Amino acid sequence: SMSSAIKSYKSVLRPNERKNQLLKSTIQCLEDGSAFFFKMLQGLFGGITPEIVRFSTEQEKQQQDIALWCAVNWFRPVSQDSLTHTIASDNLVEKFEEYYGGTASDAIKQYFSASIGESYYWNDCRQQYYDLCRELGVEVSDLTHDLEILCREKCLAVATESNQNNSIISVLFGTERDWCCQEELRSYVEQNTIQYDLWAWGEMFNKAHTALKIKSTRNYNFAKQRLEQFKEIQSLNNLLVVKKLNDFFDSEFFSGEETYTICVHHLGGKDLSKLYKAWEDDPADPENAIVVLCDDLKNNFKKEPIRNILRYIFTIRQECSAQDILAAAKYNQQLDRYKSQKANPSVLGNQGFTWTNAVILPEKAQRNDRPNSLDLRIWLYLKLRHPDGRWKKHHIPFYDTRFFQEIYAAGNSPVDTCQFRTPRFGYHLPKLTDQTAIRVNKKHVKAAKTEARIRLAIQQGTLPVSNLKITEISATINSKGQVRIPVKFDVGRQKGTLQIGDRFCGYDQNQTASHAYSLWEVVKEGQYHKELGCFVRFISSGDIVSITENRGNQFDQLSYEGLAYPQYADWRKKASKFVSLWQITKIVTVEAKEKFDAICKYQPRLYKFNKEYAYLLRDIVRGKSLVELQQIRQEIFRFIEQDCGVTRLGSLSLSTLETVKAVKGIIYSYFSTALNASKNNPISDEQRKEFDPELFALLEKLELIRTRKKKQKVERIANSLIQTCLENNIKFIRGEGDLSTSMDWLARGVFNKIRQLAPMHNITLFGCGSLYTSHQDPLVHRNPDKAMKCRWAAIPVKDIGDWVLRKLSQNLRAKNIGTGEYYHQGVKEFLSHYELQDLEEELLKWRSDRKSNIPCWVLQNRLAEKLGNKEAVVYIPVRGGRIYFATHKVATGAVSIVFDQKQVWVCNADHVAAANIALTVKG
Amino acid sequence: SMSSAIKSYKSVLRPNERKNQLLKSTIQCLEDGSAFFFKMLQGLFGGITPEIVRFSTEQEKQQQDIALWCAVNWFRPVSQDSLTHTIASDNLVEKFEEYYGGTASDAIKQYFSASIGESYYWNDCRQQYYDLCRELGVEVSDLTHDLEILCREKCLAVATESNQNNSIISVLFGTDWCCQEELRSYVEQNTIQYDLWAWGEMFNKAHTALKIKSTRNYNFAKQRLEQFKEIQSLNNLLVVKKLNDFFDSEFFSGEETYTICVHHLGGKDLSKLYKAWEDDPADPENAIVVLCDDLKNNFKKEPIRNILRYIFTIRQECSAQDILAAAKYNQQLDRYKSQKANPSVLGNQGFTWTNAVILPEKAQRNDRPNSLDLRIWLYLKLRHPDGRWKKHHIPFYDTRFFQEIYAAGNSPVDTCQFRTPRFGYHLPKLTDQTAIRVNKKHVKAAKTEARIRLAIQQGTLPVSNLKITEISATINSKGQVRIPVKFDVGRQKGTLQIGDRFCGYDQNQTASHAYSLWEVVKEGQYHKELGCFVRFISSGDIVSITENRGNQFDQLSYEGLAYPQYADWRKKASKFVSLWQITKIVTVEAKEKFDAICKYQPRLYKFNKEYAYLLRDIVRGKSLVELQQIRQEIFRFIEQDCGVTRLGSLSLSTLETVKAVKGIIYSYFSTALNASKNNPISDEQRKEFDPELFALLEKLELIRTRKKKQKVERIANSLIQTCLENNIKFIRGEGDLSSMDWLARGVFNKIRQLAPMHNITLFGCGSLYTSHQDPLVHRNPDKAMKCRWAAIPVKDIGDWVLRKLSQNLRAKNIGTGEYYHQGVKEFLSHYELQDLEEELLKWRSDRKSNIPCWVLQNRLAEKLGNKEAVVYIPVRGGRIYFATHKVATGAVSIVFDQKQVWVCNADHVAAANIALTVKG
RNA sequence: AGAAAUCCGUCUUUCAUUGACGGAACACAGGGUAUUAUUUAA
RNA sequence: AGAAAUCCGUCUUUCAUUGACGGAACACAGGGUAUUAUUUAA
């Protein structure tokens, strides 16, 4: 029982001059000792034998390679700091064979036959072990004895058996009773570092041992993976297909400045074979199959294949092959990985040192609370090492309003109680009234406000008293004075199992990166689901939103797409001016206003406008002269910094993030154009900075904005989903991920964040594999039937344009290519419902720009005849439609209709996708 | 740990001619035996003795009166059908003292000293018992002995010890008794040859009637004795004379008078009305109005204002303690004088056949491809003329019973207890390929079959999991059958735990219900009354919605079309008012009053109520020949285009409209007949005079009753669905699980009926000032209350706002007014208008010097910049409540009078208050 | 074991032969506290 | 135990000294398918 979770806090210590020097000296002492154990432990682990690896490997599920474990511990790439006995990339195998008494394994030969860091060199750890045995004055076998004991007692970590924390110090030096070298080891360590202290030696050992063990295990896995890479590297029959794929770059399809390796995912992987199969249809519109496949790949899992290279493959499709080219792409991948990725080196690292029971308890705290301001300090009582050598405890203060608010502030409520004072845990601070009168520096106002609210709560007798029962708090401090504080708490008895009455939910991600949730209940009786093996019921549906108010107006940071067209006329007007005055880009036609009009003719919202205008500015900058670029430089600055720039406005929507990316592209295109970079002179970050420092300043700021925006978006999505769970007694959450030890940054972030957050509220998280969850029919798919449907959209017939017919034709010609078939049949249903079958053949003839194309007003007249007027609503099977025709009511607000003589629920498609993940068991 | 629930079905049996005679003969035989058993059991119970009552009453929790139990069983008022030994209304005390051997108690004497039904007479049960002992050929003590044995063995029901269900028949007849043979011969001679089931049913009917009436008479006699003690308590009857001299006085124009009970005066709180009246005379009824509002808000009946106006006339002289005691005296005297004692008559209950319905799994189905077999069969034992009992099949029809249970499911995996939306199953909707062609008088039922049939072809119909082995069926002389299905539900509790979810619900002044959903949490904000930590989940409004071509109407609160959308109806109404002219002071030719309606731009149902009142007023004075045409216009009002017989939601507005239309017809009848106080009219005269209009009276009352029933059911359904969607396990409402509104009583009793079906636990409490309590602050621990506010733009502050401010300000003394008083104070302090306070104290109804509304508007516009700003005004029945915490969904945070406040839906606050109540 | 039957009801200036839905049973003198759109703009 | 300190961040043509809010930590060739109102009426 007892689920446990950790919440942590971060700040920087603010000691005075004496204590600051004490802390820095203590931390430097701890580094110096840590590096010393690093070298000595490097020698010890160099001294291990195969038999030891046998005892440590008795219990493992997978039969382990002893020779490789011995190799990774006996030879390491290290920095100059921890290098004693150098060895060359030739002598490695020769000496290994000498040490093991057998032929060097093929996997070990790959480990040795590897690229190494520029600043890292090889080291013979066994020879280091022998020289350590002399420098200790003991016989080799005595220290081998002691090492045998330590590995047995799990005092040290061996191949797959991790150590028991820091027991080695108490076992060996604190006075597992038979040592040969104990006195020598203790004197060696004590002479080289500092006088015996259990805590200090423990921290030194921990840092050194952690670095060495993680890098050794990484090298073992790396050697096996590299051997498999090599075994596949010779697999190719002939690099003829590989040369033609690589020669893609030479041909006219690629105009890019710089070349890149062609990996399997660029081709779409396995489905490219399906693509050729769809290509067998004819070359009538290879493009439609390209687009459908790419769209499906981007929707489900992998990165969308780049279309250009696939058009070039379409050029050579008959000769080269499907299997042969795709294996050729695999060859490109494997060779580049084999050559590029170096072997992991063993270097000390920059982790901090942890003081145990370092924070004074909140009830035992000392507060200088004044009536007009509380005491916002949290004190640590650390042991520090003076120059003389004695250890004494000193008080060091730090500031953290979050830690103060959630835990550290003293609550004075007689009856009220809480674990953490934060809205996600159920507590809201009383808002500030118009009597507040905060007067402090601006650079503190936010923090001051928090204090005010807390103090107000204390004044009202409202501040709840924490019930965490904290007995000790650790604190982890680094050389920069940054402190990290973990609070570990108990949550509740563990569930894990899904009974009747239990509530679960699923969540899915849109193409526009907007999330949606679907909440279900396990019921005693009703509708049966074969995958789950129980009876399910639909509770509710909705979208994930994170809302803030600005003078009473609500903005959803996660999906706000900006001002509508008519509301940013002036900004548009300024853009118009710049586009008018300036004139076209490199075919030297189109003096810019035409494109601007095209952007404005769609009447877009503000952030889409900003993205498209950023694309237009990079295009404009592209050809222009060095003297011309000065003028444009000024306008770029107003675009990025004034009135509506991404540095001033932008929500957390996908639109805003791509706008920032496009603005970065503007600056990069500026730098390329001015520098005339090409294959002869590949401009670097350094050259951009030296050339133009301020615009590099802008580039840095933009990447910073971007990173913070992504982090904030992930945190907010997780928060919104957790609140929705908390209000609806949801006990289980399912998302697109796997919990073991191909992805989107948003999908990865949200999944790992919910993994972090759900155990705090005793909510159990599951991961699954979302394959075509956008199209599966809830309660029908895999129960037991395996049923799919297409996505629809609802549009008034007055606005059926040429693109509706283009989409209809494209969906109809795509029966063979994967997700296309559901769309093909969808069009069939459409034709069956509105009785337009006669047009089908003419729709087959609908090609890109034919004059003889059946026009849209024909369709409008037929649909108006069929529905009476031009304002009636029709449903059209289109990709990424917002309407899903569900067999059952599995979305909130879904309505019931009859389409093609079939009972149907008009549902939010995204809500259907969320339900489909909620009903998934296979990951 | 296994609670039970019952769902029942009602229908009518449709046997053929032969089986119809068999069934009617069986039922008539069963009545005849039941009536015989009634007379004989009346005699047997006439023979009980005090010692028997002791032996049955030893283990009573309370102290019981044996003499009264003996008396109520020894003398009964009966109908002529079961009357044997007539006894006169004088001789009872004498004969009772003869039979008991002691002085007849005054408590027992009151039961004898009573009014009785016109067609009911007293019965000497002792002499009937004596002669029954004769006719059996036995001695008195032998049957006293067997009666003792029967009473001891819980075979018969004596005062507090209910009988065993039907052990008597098997115990006394089924094969150290003394008389067994004589009694068996007696029953079998009079009734029919021994059958355990038939004799059991006969006995059950007779015995049940007798025991209910005996216990009821015991309670009635005790209550009457206390009423007599309190009626005779009052020394000087002068004050009551002053009340009815009120009746003679001018404050009354109604056709007929009535007894003046305590609740007409406001009860206890009337004393404070004096205390309020002592404050200041000049403006008397302001305090009166406050109390009426106060009384209507709580659980009480509104005192009629007219009587208090006269009471104020005589307040100084007639006194306060004397007036309320005198009103209690009138109440007690009329109750005592005109409530009869409960008589023992056989009754119309039906007879229950056990295991009478063929199981659904063993049923015979003549299923055709275009129509299923919608018959449910019974296999009943019936008595032929020869005397033998034989089983026959009789079919009946019930689409609800068929849909929920009886139809066979063909889904491999789906399952259900009942196929109804409240239990989680929705029938597949009909497609445009359905093609139903049947009689119109069946289309609804046909539609149900179609849906079920469609569900069957799709493999969708879930298989019931009720595990039914036997079903009873209760049949009466009219062929009406009732079928109870009893099902297993789950292990309840009264132990709210952590994670348990509860809710409360309250009812508005406009009969609009609201619900508040809370959770018991491990940590957070403590509630002293509950003894736990609570958290607020959500809040809402109870709605029951139906669609009409995609437009949603809430039956519970739809107030009808908006003004501009019903011009035509108004034109007709306007024309009729135009042509016609005023009513009795015979001024004000009707149109102007009509415009008084239209100037407020009301919605349709409010318009219909007010216009119905106006037709009533018109009808009042008019001549007999004139009424000729007014009748036809009344008819169009009630029957065409928008009359209540065609439109009307379930809102309080529509019900008041129906009440007003009935008032119209009653005023018609009075006006046409020129009935008066000494020349009264009866229903018989109304029917004979104008039969068709009495037919509309019938139809209107039927509509009223059906609408009320539907409203109660829909409110219960909506609340139960809301609970089911939110894992709510507890419900709390204003009731007690054993002074009321029919809606409050009905909703509480219906939720009591429905919640145990979903393993939901219902609690009742006492809603006192729940409209004003501050959630999580009231009784935590201090008792804090607040007034109700409303939000209005300053452009529309009128004279009535100033009136309400003045009235609330002068009402510090009278109960809830105190809170409203402070509200106005807070109001002024917030808007910095304290200077006006004194002038607001001078604001009387129609003064010329009144501070006008535009002063306030100019001042408030100054304070808030514009005339479109929103201000909060303390008004009675306001829709806004200023809560200490966020205890309503959609609540916003403001600062009022330098106090942080949540603007909450007031009704939602009341629901939260009901949810946090533990004392009833 | 006999093809008939609205089980009882509700809503809508919409009364619907595919409109949408709900139900254990018993037995006061004259009435305060709008929706689609879309038009020249802000 | 020393009166200072935005812990780190987000939103808004609103940048706020009472605006509203969120967070365990580690370590490619040129862009893809509106809201308040209230005005002559229905």
Image (cartoon, coloured by chain):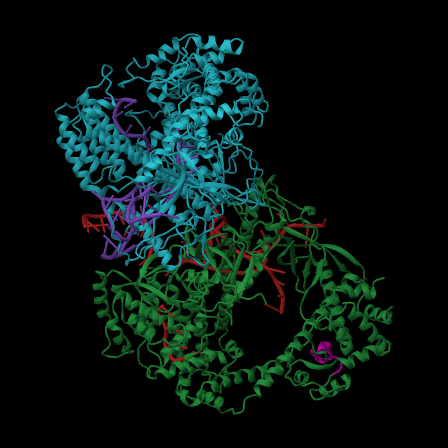
Chain colours: A cyan, B green, C red, D purple
Horizontal relation, residue B893 to residue A278: left or right: left
Q: Is residue A182 visible?
A: yes
Where's the N terminus of chain A, which quadrant? top right
Residue A904 in view of the camera? no
Residue B79 inside the magenta-drawn segment: yes
Nearer to us in this view, A549 or A150? A150
Q: Compared to B272, does A743 lie above or below?
A: above
Q: Residue at x 21, y 42 (%)?
A: A568
Residue A61 percent across, percent down from the top left: 57, 24
Q: Number of marks in the image?
A: 0
- Judge whether residue A107 is colored magenta: no
**Location of residue A322 by image quarter:** top left
B519 vs A798, nearest the viewer:
B519
Residue at 39% over, 75% down: B290
| Numbered range of the magenta stretch | B67-85
Q: Position of residue A432 (x, y in %)?
A: 31, 55
Q: Is residue D41 left or right of residue B267?
A: left
Judge by depth and name the residue closer to the eye, B65 or C26.
B65
Residue B138: percent from the left, percent from the top?
Answer: 86, 76
Instruction: Please say if C42 is above or below A839.
Output: below
Q: Is residue B820 above or below residue B549?
A: below
| Quadrant assignment, res B226 | bottom right
Q: Position of residue B794 (x, y in %)?
A: 26, 64
Q: For the point 26% across and 53% down, which residue is it?
A: A438
